[PDB]
Image (tube, rainbow, N blue to C red; front, top):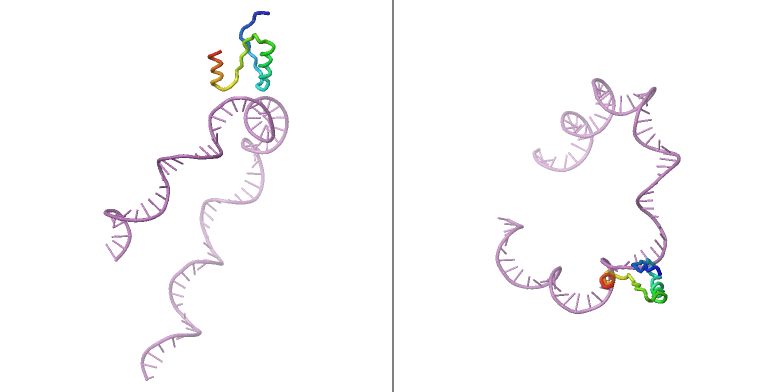
Length: 50
DNA sequence: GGATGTATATATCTGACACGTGCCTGGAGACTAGGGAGTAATCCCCTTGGCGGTTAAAACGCGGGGGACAGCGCGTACGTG
């Protein structure tokens, strides 16, 4: 609505984070929501590929 | 009849003790000041019991091969007179 489609950050506990991921998959499927967890190489993969 | 082993008595060594003496250093008495005990406040560090998540280090198993150890020879360096 307000065209503020810039970078947003949501900081959640790790145990509830699948319960946020499926909520983003269900309610806002057109959004480019990404997940940031894992070891050094997975975060590097997210950093330089996405 | 001559020579030999043992037994009590007296002089000498030898560390310890009684007495003497100096003197100086420790003790008795009085006074004082300050060092340390006690109190209160404030703030930071440590204790004991929990939780969550990362992850690198610790634990375990197994092959193998390098090294510890035992045995044997030798010759020389050290023991002995």
